Image 1 (cartoon, rainbow over the protein chains, first blue to last red):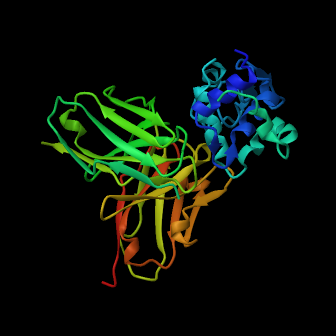
Image 2: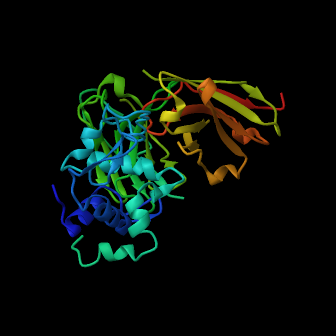
Length: 129
Length: 107
Length: 114
């Protein structure tokens, strides 16, 4: 599923990301835009053999288990397949654990490069929430 | 900090009947409210996560509802094994905080 | 499967440092975030803090920075140090993973001049 900008903003708000651990809603919408372009089925194979899965491109080396990644930690205790659903529940649950580390949203490279330091609120403006 | 207020403090019920426990947050916490059960001489047990999400291994009679500042834990047809303490906990802001608890006992 | 268990002295004196150990069996401590929670005499629960995968820690401001949570991969266990304890620190201490799925049995620690 490819979410519309406002559609995802509303969904993430329902999923409790409006002000989760100091991060405003716009951060999450912006992150999704640049990490997966709002595509829940997005996957990207990395050099180290790991793969980034879903709307928030969660990595198989540290966060989810896809059974094909060397040195897997599975910090989110969840199969990577669960992060490729049109239902964002699992991706949000895992993203919350990731951001609860001291590194915060810096875990998301696209967010760090295209969102951090910008007017992230702009990503939720002009939306019926 | 986020203050969680639970009510009633105590609730007596006859097995077979249903009950609902309340947990109110001083400030909005989204859906980041979790429910725990604790029996004497026992460690807490997670029943519901993120307001309404089910937990593998927990009886289906337990369900959670709510968002923002108002949350409820419901038990459909209370069983003897359900008597004990129930606590809500929020994870939207640090420090994580717990409600004062609701004691469920047989009437 | 995973198992957690607290260990350490059950009786300590005021002003000393209270130290507890949580031994993890079933998986490496490097695969999760680890926490400490305590229960006071009147069914009052307090989340003390947790240490995440990067080594970063989050401590409850209520502890006034008297707390330290550390890990030891080689022994697959983590710890809780609480400095200058008082009778207000008497409570049942539990270790559990961040998700709340795995908890230790809990251990009562009493702070008394006696």
